[PDB]
Amino acid sequence: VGGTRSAFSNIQAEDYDSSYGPNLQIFSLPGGGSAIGYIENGYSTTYKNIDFGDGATSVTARVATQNATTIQVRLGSPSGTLLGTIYVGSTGSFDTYRDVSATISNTAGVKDIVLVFSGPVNVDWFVFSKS
Ligand SMILES: OC[C@H]1O[C@@H](O[C@@H]2[C@@H](O)[C@H](O)O[C@H](CO)[C@H]2O)[C@H](O)[C@@H](O)[C@@H]1O
Ligand SMILES: OC[C@H]1O[C@@H](O[C@@H]2[C@@H](O)[C@H](O)O[C@H](CO)[C@H]2O)[C@H](O)[C@@H](O)[C@@H]1O
Ligand SMILES: [Ca+2]
Image (cartoon, rainbow, N blue to C red; front, top):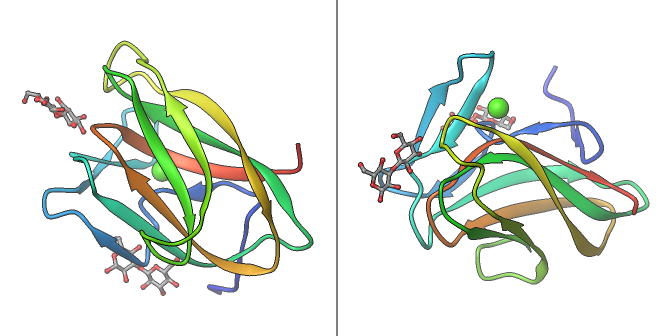
């Protein structure tokens, strides 16, 4: 139990190890599971010890928002190397979740991953893959 999490299976956004976000909340979704939300510019969540194996070059996140925003994917810390940026257009509602993807620089081994938020968005989960 609680072995190293794979980059290639969904990582629940509420399963962060550390964060910056005084108003950030975890809440239940109608369809099952939970999301993070009540996010503001400059908030972040950190996911320790994610096993990328011998590499991933894409990320997909299941997200909801009413206004275009971005989610930076960074290595180690909120000011660490920028791996890529997910562009999150409106999903019409904070309750309507859709999958959005972005390229990242090749990331391998066991790494700490940080999501850095530029504005309001709700996140259910995210996952990596080889493009
Ligand atoms: O799976 C990652 C780790 O998650 C830890 O739980 C986090 C808490 O430490 C923190 O206080 O809150 C967040 C949000 O609820 C939790 O995800 C576990 O305690 C670890 O055992 C686990 O490795
Ligand atoms: O209504 C639930 C959602 O509320 C969102 O916050 C909104 C802010 O983004 C906006 O600036 O103000 C309105 C008015 O209160 C807020 O609803 C949260 O960001 C979402 O996480 C939440 O799902
Ligand atoms: Ca979730």
